[PDB]
Image (cartoon, rainbow, N blue to C red; front, top):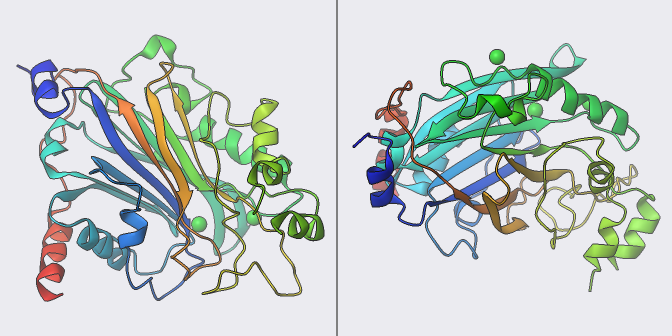
Length: 340
Ligand SMILES: [Cl-]
Ligand SMILES: [Cl-]
Ligand SMILES: [Cl-]
């Protein structure tokens, strides 16, 4: 049958569910990476093999290749880099099980800059999309406008991004009649948008400090701007977020578990989030959603979600990856594992 058809799908996914790991991390431009990425990429409850890893980074380390090399080395030879992209120091890397490269369309990327901050600094989005068998996926990572009082600007970051991301292009929309011209996130079966959205907890440092003294997370989240704005429909229309059971992932003193003890007294906040949307209700099942407290090189902790996503058979008359991946990186990862 077709490379991307029902027979192949049966061989590789009898239950038609794909295991996806999606993470976002703001690195604060740090030069030295954590000693081990094992706790980042293989979290404790990730007690089963992931099919796809998608890693979005904001304020990324200058040596993008070294970061990708360490990811490749940690995942090991069962995974290959299906795609990676950069828009300034905003990065995204997509690693997939090597036997699954055959079922992917060509991978397409797009970028949007939503705010010029200075001559050398901007905020924006990086989107990567491809079809897997017959099901299309769109991954967007973003760094939104910063500041407690800048919700209105964050709304504009959302709107500018869904209006401007030029995806898909060569690879056909899988359900075009369902698509809207004004929102790129309507053009795909499964959408994940993860980043430093910079939404904060309202109420001020003193009130949030009081709440953090067991922590009642639900009560804490009553102060979250992002849940508030999503609830009234002003942002991320059609998206959901998994339940949060972890503590705020920002702002931390470097290398420590204490929240910003400088005079600026930034209110601990859930700046880093993973959101999902699907064309078909129920296609995406969150399995776990958490931060990685052991990664402490940056003022932000990484945040990741594990998901199970439904996939459907496809056809071969689209532009195909057909075994295309970063072979040089793959070899570098092999080389590093021989060394260590
Ligand atoms: Cl960035
Ligand atoms: Cl573009
Ligand atoms: Cl900003």
